[PDB]
Image (cartoon, rainbow, N blue to C red; front, side):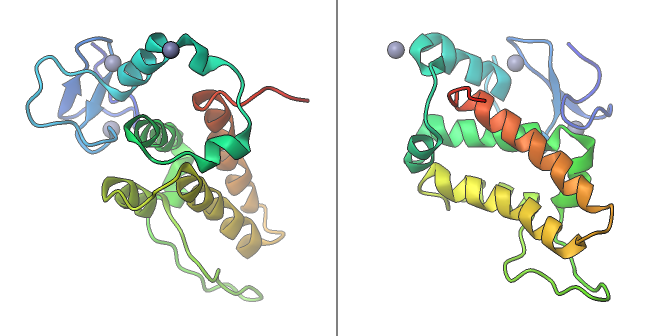
Length: 178
Ligand SMILES: [Zn+2]
Ligand SMILES: [Zn+2]
Ligand SMILES: [Zn+2]
């Protein structure tokens, strides 16, 4: 197995996947690495299994259909994995914890949002459809772009949104377009 966490790239107290060489900190994995379970399979492995059981699930889909899906177990897992893919980028640090807004010439967003809040909401089963999760994720970056205006720091929001959107299109097999 790897000797660093797949998500944060640090060593420490790591749990090892039984079906692949990845390793994780307990609360870096999403969901948090389970208490017992021998063998244990990581989220990457569980997602690959879904795909392998239903090869047709990789054919292209319309976003509008994906967003209306109810959060049954497989869609719950897919959103957990998409959230984890965001955390895998080191620039996610800017969006992880609760933000605050005190900048001359800007006003804070009406509905603040952050990764750890989305994480809690998934854990607590607060989303009934994929749309709920995707809306909160996109809100993180939209709030950032609007608050930071012309400051070059707005680019961090563009960068992390691009990670989110590419992973969304991959995980939910969105139909490729120009
Ligand atoms: Zn970690
Ligand atoms: Zn694995
Ligand atoms: Zn099938």
